[PDB]
Length: 218
Image 1 (cartoon, rainbow, N blue to C red):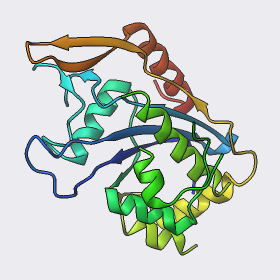
Image 2 (cartoon, rainbow, N blue to C red; image 1 turned 180 degrees about the vertical axis):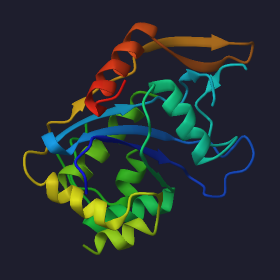
Image 3 (spheres, helix red, strand yellow; image 1 turned 90 degrees about the horizontal axis):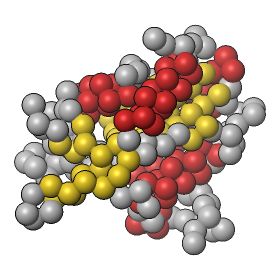
């Protein structure tokens, strides 16, 4: 595996059976990796962020009207960086994969936790707990667990690469991820009061530059 930096979009569903306005994603987390330098940054995109979908401006419910490929292109558009790898997991598949690696501890407002727990252990308060979980999973190992956990998710991360990665990132990596944030305010629209997260322009542009530089990308 080359050691060029690259991005991963983790998308969390409930379905795999998504169809109407009810297919939407629950979690969107982006990680950027720079293997050569054993680095990593991480970003959470709040479900209600108000974006142009890949022309009104709606939440990032691009999965519902296009599936994975739409969420990916919306996110690329929103972050101005290429998404190289993706990972989509269900509610079960999630719980599952956690059991697999052995479960893991977090923290809670520490303790271990079972698929069901962590799974239920989970805007912007939910968001902190999700990175918590990812963060725990990443620490939970910094050979078959892959094969299994992998055939349970939509992804384009091959086996060789995954193994190459936990190998490169065994050393130096635990609570070091440079975690970024999308900062915005509340915006309510219409009578019924449909809620939107409106991201702060200024921060967005600093998040973009940060990631762009980490991917070595203009």
